[PDB]
Amino acid sequence: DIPDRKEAVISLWPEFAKAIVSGKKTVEFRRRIPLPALSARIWIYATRPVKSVIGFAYLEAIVQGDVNTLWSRYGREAFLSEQQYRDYFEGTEKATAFLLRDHQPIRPINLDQLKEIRANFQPPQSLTWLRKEETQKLVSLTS
Ligand SMILES: [Cl-]
Ligand SMILES: [Cl-]
């Protein structure tokens, strides 16, 4: 029984995780990774020291294309220096741009609660898809 990928979790360092949930960062760049559904809700897991899901946002678009064109068009909305961007994309010619909308902060759901939802949860290297019963438990914890 395969997840539909309309619900996914992504990991960011806490300054960037907070920028997405506050609506300051509306673009997240990644390499060519397996993609979520276009209508997905993306729950934002902040890594140490926060180690918590701190909110979510939705996708208005997924863009893939040349690394230079993605920087020129969307880099201003991504909250990262051009240097951090060039360093992350060294070694590939193409990138993914996740364009986000409708960000929502929540009271943080810590890693102990997350392991109560999925026993071996650990922060994803890219995306992880939530199963429907996992999603029902996470929505139940939201404030
Ligand atoms: Cl990667
Ligand atoms: Cl670890």
Image (cartoon, rainbow, N blue to C red):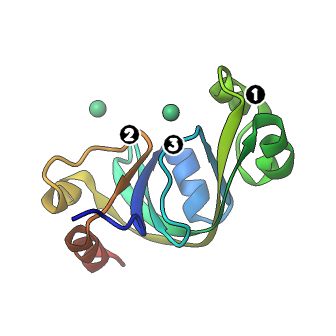
- Measured as percent of width and height from the top left, residue 51 is found at 34, 47
Q: Nearer the viewer, residue 137 or 95?
A: 95
Ligand 2 is found in which quarter of the picture? top left
- Identify the element where label 3 is drawn: loop
Viewport quadrant of the C terminus: bottom left
Q: Is mark 3 within 8 Å of ligand 1?
A: yes
Q: Nearer the viewer, residue 24 or 8?
A: 8
Mark 1 surroundings within 10 Å by alpha-carbon count, few (fewer than 14), some (14 through 19), many (20 or more): few
Viewport quadrant of the N terminus: bottom left
Which amino acid, mark 3? Answer: Ile
Q: Is residue 132 above or below residue 32?
A: below
Which residue position is annotated with label 1?
83
> Disc 2 to disc 3, how far (Cα)?
23 Å
Q: Earlier in the sequence, mark 2 or mark 1?
A: 2
Which residue position is annotated with label 2?
48
Which residue position is annotated with label 3?
33
Residue contact at pointers 2 and 3, CB within 8 angstroms = no
Q: Is mark 2 within 8 Å of ligand 2?
A: no
